[PDB]
Length: 70
Length: 70
Image (tube, rainbow over all chains, first blue to last red; front, top):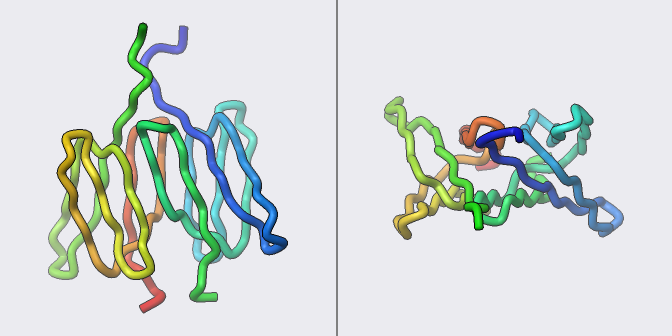
C-alpha cells in the first residue's frame, strides 16, 4: 500500500453561516487575505477572509475561522 | 489492529529572534491573541502574538507566523 503517511479533513463556515467540509487534505496555507486547501487527488480550494483556527493530529481535523483584521 | 494515530512538529520564532521547535504535537489552537500547543504526553506550550501560517499533513509540520491584528 501507500506506506507511512498522514492526511486530514478541513471544516469551515461561509459568510452565509453555512458549514463546508473538505476530505483527504494533505496541506493547508494561510495567505495574506485567504486560506488555501489541497487534496491527495491534487484538487485545490481557496476561501477569502478566513484564518486557520485549530489543528488535531489524533482526529485528523483542521478548523478554519473568519479573520477580523480585514 | 493497526495504529490510526498521527503527530506533528511545530516551528516558530521569538520576539528576541530565537528559533523554537516542538516535537510530538497532538493538537494546536489559535486563540484571539496567542497560539497554544499540546503534546502526545500531556505537556503544553503557549505563545502570545502568533497565528497558524501552514499545516502540512504530508510532512507532519505546522508553522507559526507573527500576528498583524494587534
